[PDB]
Amino acid sequence: LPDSDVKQALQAIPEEFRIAVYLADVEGFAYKEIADIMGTPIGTVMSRLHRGRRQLRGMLEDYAR
Image (cartoon, rainbow, N blue to C red):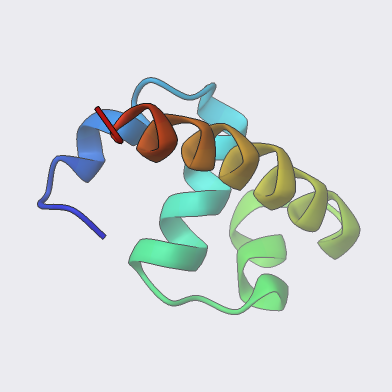
């Protein structure tokens, strides 16, 4: 999306969602591999990705002057 102003949006999000989002959307990991990394049910990984992307969307919307 924007610049690596991303590390900075992401850091504004709770740790749990932030890691799911970084791993999925910055690093390109598969939800099943992220479930291994995080040691959580894949369905938990998905729920954090949704909450996490929800917030994120909320920021780049604000970044519409």
